[PDB]
């Protein structure tokens, strides 16, 4: 029945994360915090407008707002939430910074599944080691509301079985061509309640269901990068125009997790 905090997080949960590449941590945010953070995200959606992850209006996987935490004063306290970010730190076992966050919405009956990938491939960064994502549920997410699934142990893939980095979208390859054994790997669906968080490593292969429920799904994805991460040109780097290749990502836009 009780909250999970950075302090009371079990050694078993940390071991599960290190071995499996993901972990479900329940009850990190209270009902009150969920309500306040969801409302702030709704304000950002209204003010910024959403973007489509997918191939146009008829092939929406996810509606999103990128660098989302920067776009509302109250969202700083989400990405640097003491429990969420403190748990991320314990799981990673190394110093972290906030890279970015996204508002991640799936509308009911109008979404495709989120196509399988690892996050490393689309991060415009060098020097990744312990980088991981906190996928924070701001609504309940039973399976059919667009829940996440993960391939256990896939973060430990050898180099030849990983794509690593896309400089441009022409480099896209089907995961089965990159990782021939992909289709014979188990796939774990992890439904969650609002306020729960699932963390996954930047090499963990993952995906999400279509939302075929009657209710909107909203999560908030926070990418916590290695604290000494540097800039590497790639797809998804439009907001990093002020940087040169190899420059460290530091300062107020990429704050240290303490
Ligand atoms: O919310 C989704 O459907 C996709 C999430 C995702 O890929 C991530 O958090 O890395
Ligand atoms: Fe992802």
Image: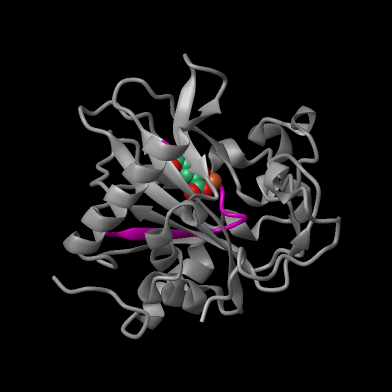
Q: Which residues are magenta?
A: 195-208
Image point (28%, 74%), residue name: 4
Indicate left or right for 189 with 231 as reference: left
Could you tell me which quadrant the N terminus lies in?
bottom left
Indicate left or right for 257 with 45 as reference: right
* 244 falls in the magenta region: no
Note whether residue 87 is visible.
yes
Indicate left or right for 235 with 45 as reference: right
Q: Residue 192 versus residue 179: which sits nearer the camera?
A: 192
- Residue most toward the top? 58
Image point (39%, 63%), residue name: 78
- Compared with 158, 76 (above or below) is below
Number of disc labels: 0
- Residue most toward the left? 1
Q: Residue 10 versus residue 151: which sits nearer the camera?
A: 10
Note whether residue 187 is visible.
no
- Compared with 219, 76 (above or below) is below
- Residue most toward the right? 245
User: Residue 200's spot in the image, x, y percent?
Assistant: 50, 58
Residue 66 quadrant: top right
User: Residue 25's spot in the image, x, y percent?
Assistant: 33, 65
Indicate left or right for 177 with 29 as reference: right
Image point (47%, 38%), residue name: 48
Q: Residue 29 versus residue 175: which sits nearer the camera?
A: 29
- Compared with 2, 173 (above or below) is above
User: Residue 194's spot in the image, x, y percent?
Assistant: 24, 53
User: Residue 128's spot in the image, x, y percent?
Assistant: 71, 63
Indicate the colouring scheme. Answer: one colour
- Residue most toward the bottom? 7
């Amino acid at each position: 029945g009780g909250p999970t905090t950075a302090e009371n997080l079990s050694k078993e949960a940390v071991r599960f994360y290190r071995e499996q590449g993901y972990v479900h941590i329940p009850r990190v945010l209270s009902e009150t915090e969920v309500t306040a953070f969801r409302a702030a995200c709704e304000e950002v959606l209204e003010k910024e407008g959403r973007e489509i992850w997918g191939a146009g209006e008829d092939e929406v996987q996810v509606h999103y707002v990128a660098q989302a935490w920067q776009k509302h004063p109250e969202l700083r306290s989400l990405v640097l939430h003491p429990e969420i970010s403190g748990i991320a730190l314990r799981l990673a076992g190394a110093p972290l910074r906030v890279y970015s966050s996204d508002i991640l919405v799936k509308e009911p009956k109008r979404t495709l599944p989120t196509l399988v990938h690892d996050d490393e491939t689309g991060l415009p960064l060098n020097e990744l080691s312990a980088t991981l994502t906190a996928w924070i549920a701001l609504t309940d997410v039973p399976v059919e509301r667009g829940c996440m699934s993960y391939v256990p142990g896939s973060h430990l893939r050898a180099r030849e079985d990983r794509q690593e980095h896309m400089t441009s979208f022409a480099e896209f390859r089907d995961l089965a061509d990159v990782w021939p054994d992909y289709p014979w790997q188990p796939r774990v669906a992890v439904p969650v309640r609002a306020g729960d968080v699932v963390f996954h490593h930047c090499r963990t292969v993952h995906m999400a269901e279509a939302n075929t429920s009657d209710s909107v799904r909203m999560a908030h994805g926070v990418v916590y990068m290695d604290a000494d991460a540097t800039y590497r040109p790639g797809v998804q780097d439009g907001h990093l125009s002020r940087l040169s290749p190899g420059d460290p990502l530091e300062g107020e836009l990429f704050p240290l997790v303490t």
